[PDB]
Image (cartoon, rainbow, N blue to C red; front, side, top):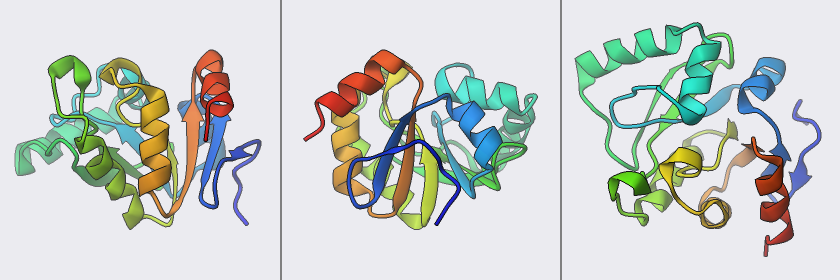
Length: 167
């Protein structure tokens, strides 16, 4: 039993809710919240900008030190950093950004990072300002992640479309 509430069960291990991931993280304080990161960990907008804003920019400060030490992530890769006031840990995962021309096949590699964590609160990777089809992202999630994932979808209209079209 865990503390996640109000989710629709899609499969054995994937759950979904119309929710603001920031507000959901603040209430649940999950072990892991996933950020929709870019390779530079520049948290300017989308989910990343919202998560970082909720940390009062502490996520960005920590991220800048990470990049200065380690260099950029790979598209499809990830790193574990602090969850600050939102979670124990933040798993920064880089899905391909279609608006930069990155290969969508890398979306499966991106979701594979979730399998290193037993339970996660996450957005749909490569959705929103990353330009991929969220219906496709949900399909890849279900077909790739084997650990327990709680997906937060900000847009109510999109949430209803994802549920109604789910196979």
